[PDB]
Amino acid sequence: ENAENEGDALLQFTAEFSSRYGDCHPVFFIGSLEAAFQEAFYVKARDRKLLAIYLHHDESVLTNVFCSQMLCAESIVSYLSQNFITWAWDLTKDSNRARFLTMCNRHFGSVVAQTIRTQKTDQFPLFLIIMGKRSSNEVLNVIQGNTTVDELMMRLMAAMEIFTAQQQEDI
Image (cartoon, rainbow, N blue to C red; front, side, top):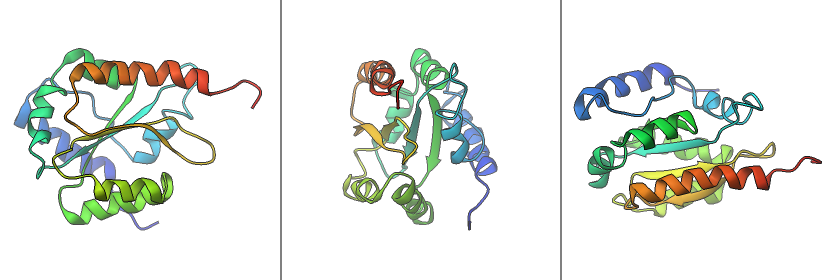
């Protein structure tokens, strides 16, 4: 379908963000969002993990601090990247803004995208967590952004223990 190169697009960002903020940062997966999913759910039953979309919005005043505030920790970045799948998407410009909405609209749903529209800008960054379902990808938790780095730890770790319990063996 009509789409633009993601991998490269992300690279340029990862490269800048590196210097802009600093070397210390969570390993950003280079490729197409599609993979960020398969490599999470469709991944080896052993390498099974969860995905976490990190929306980066300049307009937001937090996105700045939150970066060196929460995305500054080594345990969070290392764990979020190792345990979970770290993925960033620059939706600053409208062009990108809509794009994402369109993708999520289907991938996730209409009730999901709409929410993003209501979610103010300050709230950002918006950290979402997906469990993954053959039928369709659905989120389990949606953090505004003014949360505490600590909350992220439990929020992430929990999503893991919860998932295992959610899924079944028969079905």
